[PDB]
Amino acid sequence: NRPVALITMATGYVGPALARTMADRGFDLVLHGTAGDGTMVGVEESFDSQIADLAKRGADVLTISDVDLTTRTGNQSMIERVLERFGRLDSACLVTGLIVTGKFLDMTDDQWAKVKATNLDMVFHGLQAVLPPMVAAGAGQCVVFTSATGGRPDPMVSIYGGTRAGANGIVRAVGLEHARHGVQVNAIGTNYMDFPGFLKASRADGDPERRAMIEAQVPLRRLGTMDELSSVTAGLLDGSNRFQTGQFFDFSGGWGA
Amino acid sequence: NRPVALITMATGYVGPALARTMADRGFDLVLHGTAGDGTMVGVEESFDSQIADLAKRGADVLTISDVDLTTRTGNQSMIERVLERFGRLDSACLVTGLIVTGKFLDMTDDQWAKVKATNLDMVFHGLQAVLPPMVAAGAGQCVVFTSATGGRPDPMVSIYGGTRAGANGIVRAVGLEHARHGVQVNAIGTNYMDFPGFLKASRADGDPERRAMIEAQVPLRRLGTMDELSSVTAGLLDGSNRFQTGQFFDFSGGWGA
Amino acid sequence: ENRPVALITMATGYVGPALARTMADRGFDLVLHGTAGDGTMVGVEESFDSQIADLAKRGADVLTISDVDLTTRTGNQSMIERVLERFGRLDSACLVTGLIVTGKFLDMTDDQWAKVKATNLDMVFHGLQAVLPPMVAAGAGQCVVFTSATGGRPDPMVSIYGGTRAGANGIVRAVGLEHARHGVQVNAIGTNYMDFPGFLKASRADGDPERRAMIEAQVPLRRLGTMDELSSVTAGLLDGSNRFQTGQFFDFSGGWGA
Amino acid sequence: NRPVALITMATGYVGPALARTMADRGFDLVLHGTAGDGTMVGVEESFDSQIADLAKRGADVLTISDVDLTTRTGNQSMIERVLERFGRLDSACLVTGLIVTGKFLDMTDDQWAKVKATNLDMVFHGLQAVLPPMVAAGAGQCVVFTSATGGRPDPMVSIYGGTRAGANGIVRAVGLEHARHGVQVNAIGTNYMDFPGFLKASRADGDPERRAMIEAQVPLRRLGTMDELSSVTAGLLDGSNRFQTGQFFDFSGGWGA
């Protein structure tokens, strides 16, 4: 009678570490992500890599990789397949958004359309899909991964940070609107996290000089690890804490304080 | 040589009062709004009624009413017409957004698409249009009218309040990004304002008992007047204050404090 | 006839003089608290005597007060008593508060800690407890408490100053909301990078063009604010033209606190 | 070689539960609190009761109960005694403050002096005492318990909530100032917590009708438990999360969102 946790984009970012710890805490898992092996873009830990490890930890796993999470149908389909496999949805970790930077006046209509689709549509359709079963069950926990930029939308990240702030605002209203049904919805916004995506984007991957310069921008003078983040995230998804909802948590080494 | 102020949606909301005070302060005006007489929806003060008054106050007026301010072309065309008429743009008051309320899970794809177009596209394309001439001049003042809900996105107004928070976030980044060019961009978010639109929506227009209950929700126990709001708004657009940018100002009788 | 009355503290420096002029232009009589002396005395940027003549030309009666300790109940209560005695009314109050202290948190002494509480908090608590009763009784009033932009972003090297400024803003929020129903507004303005002798001397930018440029470089709008700008915003919250904001904090630092 | 965690006011509030979990996580403990049995005011779990339980969990315990934590001497002496017994200080949970409510204009000079001493002096002297050894060690984690009222200082809680906001502000600056030394300092502000103190103050301790009205004020329609709070608190003190500092975390069932 294990509870069920959904994790999207689970082939990279916090998904793998979160899956391991959520399995340690007695959860069955539905992992949405990108199909293929490590060579494929955006695959930091392949599905096949994880299935064996999570099985050892006692978790059943369902993988999903043929849905468009910027759309209603994609998210509705994803949840339909969760309920089909395990008849229940207790926790949901919705990873959203795609980075875009540059001068505000250089932003194209395509960049504007893309950032709305990744930073907002994923949140709107994601929440409209995970909530109904949680409300029906009278209990549920959701974490929406936005960005620490949402807490301080800065120059050169206008449309990305701004829409992240809108995502946090949606999460606040939704987290408060369904609190009375026993459902929690909170947002985590990270920055300066140590995973291949950020290292490649920041050009720190193979450059120690660049790495030191990036870390110097962080008050704690380091990059965050996925084990740390997964521990905090799991804390909001494992049922141990049921007294926070509609809130935004900065996780950027103090950068967003 | 008089400075020039742009005001959108100027046939209702704060536009008319703002136009009068901005003219008193020595500005020529470009008024975007709805073409018609009082009978047309969204026309609280027609162009023709205002032009006579603003002329007495010494202001030349250019009217615009055939542009789609949710698009790049509409906003770019509007500013092109401002510049051909008056060769300069000193101040811009961009009124944006359209109210939508209801349970989060009842929101349709159309409502979601509409709120993004009114609360976000208007801001993105509006700012991309007004800023270039201000940057070129090394001076400019912009106020983006969002909503007090952006400061506290609450249940029953999730996607509206949330996107308003995103609009405020964009304003913050943009206001900071172009500060070094001598350009200010700030946001004002109102609520419980005394104008026919809100009165009709709140159903208090002809019900004194209804109004007293609405006023009871406001700490200052009253509704704001457009003359008050126009005075505050003009303070951010008349050149008297050049030391605030990237900021959001709540104007809701303390409701958003 | 029947001019409204505005109280301004610390009016011999900072925003007081400019605020007094504009408030007089807007038809207010004035009570100016400040430091007694001429320009040579510390903390006197515009002496009472300098202002008395100008404000009279603008049509304002002036009462000066300079023998009260505004960190205490007695000082603030006495100040308001003397306002009501001279003009029977108090319509607006601009309470300038606080005294700068900086340095490493672990270097702060008990005296610095005691001083920052007295200037940044006691002035606000006793100031508001004194100005509010007459406003509540009249059913109308407007108050601005000058705190600091550091209250919006308490940073390293400004821990106890910025932190207590944040507490002052918090008190202003609760009080501004608590007495809103009586028709009284209480808001806070927090400034930084203002162009007045105090800041120029403190920042060491006085007579140092390179230093001045460096300080301005820290401001998004790449400049220092002027008292005429600040007094215009401040008066807007004290002249009765805007009666729909209370319990709020307004950053005034060229975007530094955005 | 166990790490050392200091917990103040450990005879009530979160202290006992936090001590248990921190012991489970391999910490030695120093508990400051009130000396006595349950009959004494403010004693919910006596020292003697806890020591036996904590000993079973593998923790050495040092008790301290004759210091005035509103003063420099009290806090410095407390930390000296911590270092004397265990030569190290890794984590510190500084519980601070004392509730006071009423109309702002009814507050006396004694109430004003008391709230400054409990809500601010405890924080200033507390941090000045715990930080030096953590800086010297190049690592440390501190949680300062303030109040959810600090996030929204409301009428009838002016001086309490306001000073709580100042405490959070100090924590932000201090948490950012010593981040480069590997030290974290964060604040947690609670409300609507289920413990005898709050139940007695709210008069709900024996009135289910009163309690049901209390829970109705909370978005999640419940009171928080110390086990939940201790789990979140321990998460910021057990070394598992070293990427948050200078931050304030609301823990009030969404009341402070």
Image (cartoon, coloured by chain):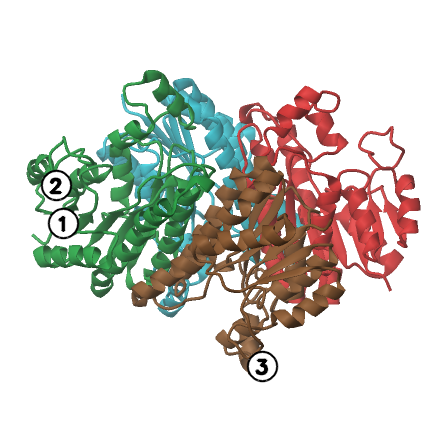
Chain colours: A red, B cyan, C green, D brown
Q: Which residue is mark 3?
A: D208
Crowd around label 1: few <14 · some 14–19 · many ≥20 (10 Å): few
Q: Chain of mark 1?
A: C
* Residue B81 place in picture, x, y as percent: 43, 24
* Residue C118 place in picture, x, y as percent: 31, 50
Q: Which residue is mark 1?
A: C67
* Residue C93 place in picture, x, y as percent: 23, 51
In the rendered view, would you say D40 is above or below A8?
below
* Residue at image point 50% right, 26% down: B76
On the question of residue B100 being in view, the answer is no
* Residue A189 place in picture, x, y as percent: 63, 42
Mark 3 touches mark 2? (CB < 8 Å): no
Crowd around label 2: few <14 · some 14–19 · many ≥20 (10 Å): some
Mark 1 touches mark 3? (CB < 8 Å): no
> Are labels 3 and 2 on one chain?
no
Find numbered disc 2 in the image and state the secondary structure of the residue it sits on: loop
Q: Which residue is mark 2?
A: C36
Whole-number angstrom distance, CA of label 1 to CA of label 3 = 56 Å
Mark 1 touches mark 2? (CB < 8 Å): yes
Depth check: C95 or D45 in front? D45
Depth check: C110 or A26 in front? C110
Crowd around label 3: few <14 · some 14–19 · many ≥20 (10 Å): few
Residue type at numbered disc 1: Asp
Depth check: C125 or B228 in front? C125
Depth check: D42 or D73 in front? D73
* Residue at image point 74% right, 46% down: A230
> Are labels 1 and 3 on one chain?
no
Q: Earlier in the sequence, mark 1 or mark 2?
A: 2
